[PDB]
Structure formats: C-alpha cells, structure tokens
Length: 225
Ligand code: SF4
Image (cartoon, rainbow, N blue to C red; front, side):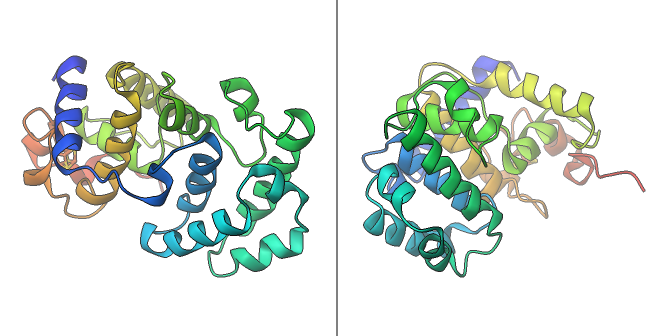
C-alpha cells in the first residue's frame, strides 16, 4: 500500500468513526494537547478525562500551573500514577513561564526542549493543536506501522526505531495532519491492539502485511531473550 493510499484511507476512516469530541479536542491549544498527551502516556483515556477536566479548571493556563506549588500539582495528580510525569509537567510549565513569557511554544525545538516532552510528544502537540507537519510515533502508532509494513525487529533497537520513524514520516500527510495523527493513535489504541487486533474494523486491512499473513503477533518484534 502506497503512502498516499495509507493516509487517504486513515483520513476517510477518521471522518466516519474517529472520536473528535474529547475535552482536549475542543478549542485545542498547545497547552491542552500537551497536558492531555502527558496524562495519556501511561494512563487509559477513561481514567484521564476527570483529571484533565480538574486540571484545566484549576489551571486554566500554563502560567497558573507554573505558579502553583508542586505539592498542589502532585495532590491533584493523585491516582494517575507515574508521578515523574507530574514533576516534569510542573518544571516544563515553569520553563514556559520563565523562557517563553507564559505562551506555550509553537516551534518544535522549543517544545522538545521541555522536560517530559519527547520527539513524538512535541510532534503531537504542534500537529494536533496547530496542524504543523510533524509525524508521531508512540507504542500504539509503532504497532500499526510495524504490522502494516512487517517490521519484525525490536523497537528498542536504534535501527528499528529509525526505520519506524521513516515509515511514519512517509505516511504522514501535511494536509489534514491533525486528523491523521489523532486517527493513528485511535487505531493503535482501539483497533490494532497488542492482542487479537480487530483487523476487519481496520482501514488498513486491505494492504496490511500482518493481516494478509495473520502474523500480527510477530510485529513489532519483542526484546530478545
Ligand atoms: S489490519 Fe490488523 S494488524 Fe494490520 S494495522 Fe489493521 S488492526 Fe493492525
């Protein structure tokens, strides 16, 4: 399946089935996308929604989050687990207030410079909130790509990771990137699951290698032992 076909089929799918009404999808801003991405990294969406709403109410802007005492941030985070995310979240908020005048950065370099923000997250923030042309690659997106293009190596390996980043770059369009990237995350989270993927409900089923050979269990490769 060519790249043009890949994005086109994903976009058509998103239009008809994709969720576009979550709290962090309404009146999107870099701040809301960032906050949600960090909460979603290690936590299920259902659990995240109430916390996101509580955070946005208490911290309407990044400067409000920055000026707040860390103890208050951790108290509100209670129940989400993986508190390192919270600690970095607060530091990043303070970095935005200090270095960027309270305006969450809208350029890749500045975003990726924040604590707790990686290449994929920075790309997600700018693409989802401003439509900037950046590809993403988290565990969910990587699984979809690895299966579709049969990448059997372990993503923990440098060459494999770079290979997956190349594939994401190839299929990610500029036109409609905000929709494409959200769709990819949705597919990997709801359709292309680790176990028994719902291939019949997948928009890439007609070109996916793993589906053609019923070999989804081989991709991505597991850490050798
Ligand atoms: S067809 Fe199946 S294995 Fe392939 S990307 Fe879709 S859900 Fe994953």
